[PDB]
Amino acid sequence: ATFEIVNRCSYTVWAAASKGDAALDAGGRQLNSGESWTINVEPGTNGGKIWARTDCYFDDSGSGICKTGDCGGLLRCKRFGRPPTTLAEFSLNQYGKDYIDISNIKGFNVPMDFSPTTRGCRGVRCAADIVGQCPAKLKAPGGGCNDACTVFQTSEYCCTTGKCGPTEYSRFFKRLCPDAFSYVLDKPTTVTCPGSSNYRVTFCPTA
Image (cartoon, rainbow, N blue to C red):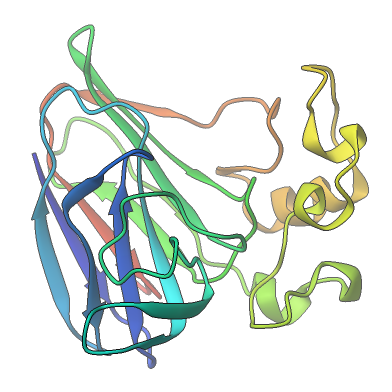
């Protein structure tokens, strides 16, 4: 499958693509404002994620650190990123279908649209100004808005019992972005697309 990753932000993002134990395609790439990166994601991929990283410092070897979404200090991500990270999440070719969503469960850093290229399903978007509205206690020191589980590390927020409901902090994200997951047991906002669809992930969407 094809995923076009497009940076329409006024700032650079270091795009990342991983399925948690491995890179998808090259795993990461610097996208200056206006740049795009088209990757191939293998059919059958489950638990794939694409996200933006902001304010990265990499040396010539591709090692360093990002202020949001850092993946083990690498330019080319193999693992998932440090919160806060707006997440484009997908599993492909699952019983004939693809499944896509956006999640704020690990916080929000960059506004995102995640849409199919085909007409056979809809896209989803979380592009409200969550960082500008972020409650003080959730503000992340390098930018972005942490989820409450990251900040407080209690079962109320982390759902580590498999038993949790909405909170004032999940509702902060959910009201701003109803189409994104705001906590683990949120009413699902996963979209069913035709199997073997192609997609576009847009940072700072306007269309």
